[PDB]
Amino acid sequence: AKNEIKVYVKNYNARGNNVGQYIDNALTINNFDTIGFSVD
Amino acid sequence: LGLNPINDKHLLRPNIVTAELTDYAGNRLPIDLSLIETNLEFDSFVTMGAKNEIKVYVKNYNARGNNVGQYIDNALTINNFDTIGFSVDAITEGHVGYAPLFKQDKFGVHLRLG
Amino acid sequence: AITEGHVGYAPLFKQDKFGVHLRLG
Amino acid sequence: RSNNDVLATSTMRVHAIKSELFTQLEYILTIGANLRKSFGTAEKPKFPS
Amino acid sequence: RSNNDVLATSTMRVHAIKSELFTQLEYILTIGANLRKSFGTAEKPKFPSSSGSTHDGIYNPYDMYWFNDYESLKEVMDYLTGYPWIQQSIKNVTIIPSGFIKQESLNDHEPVNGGDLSVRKLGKQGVSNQKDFNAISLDYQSLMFT
């Protein structure tokens, strides 16, 4: 439905074992390729 | 916070403790604990149906109570709600927001005590 | 048609907060 | 609590987390037609405002 | 580790690099027509409405069709050229990285229009793999090591 991988670092800035910043500190990927086609 | 409530009230200051709200979608709210007179109470200001938006504020923040403080001028404001697509004989599309967060049980407002 | 309404200070007013406020500090 | 009279401090960490989770959901189906009166059929359509 | 009690230091350099490389790929062919029932012919066209699936808790009015081989997708992209009124309703074909889709989020190989070809509807309510990225992760020992 929606194409996006954001990869985070586990328990960053956290005093574990709670999650830290979780995804508020993530490298976020979503410029995926789409492919063109032809029709008549 | 592991603070002794009986004689450590003078330690509720930003360089010892910090509070932040987030919806894990980039909407955030920083909080300066030196400004809550005695209670970290979160109330909200939600309008629905016609316009969908929940903004959650902190009660009497920076206030010398019992007047309201910043009220909603200091609020974590939520309104990227999901809509759902359907088909007809058009195909008009759904909008995605907090959905995949919810299938991880993280759709919600979170507080980070530091 | 169904031409839509615009919302601004409305839900503020149903909480009696539609108005201009002064913060003396 | 406000003055800058405090000791050099550098080691803040996310100490605890509490959260009001949205556990169940509700829905508004917002359409421009009165869903609770006669539609009709394909050949004879009615459009309740 | 946090205080400013450390010696004057100036000579940082990119010491090492680890990377989780996207080695193989997968494809979602996301169109607004039910690829797996009758299209018809040029003179008598039928337009099967897209059923809709639900992945990662988002309902799609469209059909999402899975492919983990280019050739598989090509064979179907080609089969589709002979039906410009069904092909008309493609939103895109996206290229994603491998191993992010759960097998039990995929229907089995159902036949296309006729068909000689099979396509796998992606739905079944399921989520994606919340992948543990390990090629790039260093446990304590391994970190201090590297």
Image (cartoon, coloured by chain):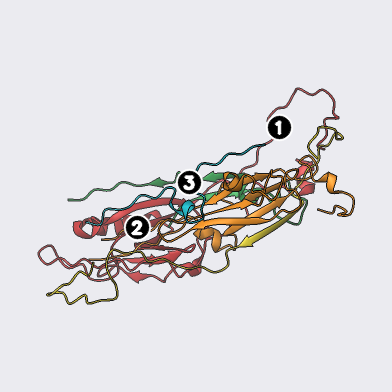
Q: Which residue is mark 2?
A: B93
Residues at marks 3 and 2, CA–CA distance in whole angstroms: 19 Å
Please provide percent x and percent y for residue E55: 46, 63
Position of C5 relative to E56 (above/below): above
Marks 3, 1 in one chain: no
Labels 1, 2: front one:
2
Q: C4 left or right of E39?
A: right
Marks 3, 2 in one chain: no
Q: Which residue is mark 1?
A: E15
Instruction: Please name the amino acid that badge 1 sits on.
Output: His
- Color used for chain E? red
Please provide percent x and percent y for residue B93: 34, 57
Instruction: Please name the amino acid that badge 2 sits on.
Output: Glu
- Color used for chain C? cyan
Q: D43 left or right of E55?
A: left
Labels in figure, total? 3
Q: Is residue A38 visible?
A: yes
Circle 3 — which element? loop
Mark sitting on residue B72: none
Which chain is green in the rendering?
A
Q: Is residue E131 visible?
A: no
Structural crowding at the residue carrying mark 1, measured as other residues with C-alpha within 10 Å and reported as few (<14), some (14–19) or many (≥20): few
- Give the residue displayed 21% in from the left and 66% down from the top: E47
Q: Chain of mark 1?
A: E
Please provide percent x and percent y for residue B55: 55, 52
- Give the residue displayed 31% in from the left and 46% down from the top: A36
**Circles 3 and 2: CB atoms closer than 8 Å:** no
Mark sitting on residue A30: 3
- Which of the pair E126/B79 is nearer the observer? B79
- Give the residue displayed 49% in from the left and 45% down from the top: C19
- Which of the pair E110/D35 is nearer the observer? D35
Q: Report the residue that reaches farthest toward the right.
A: B7
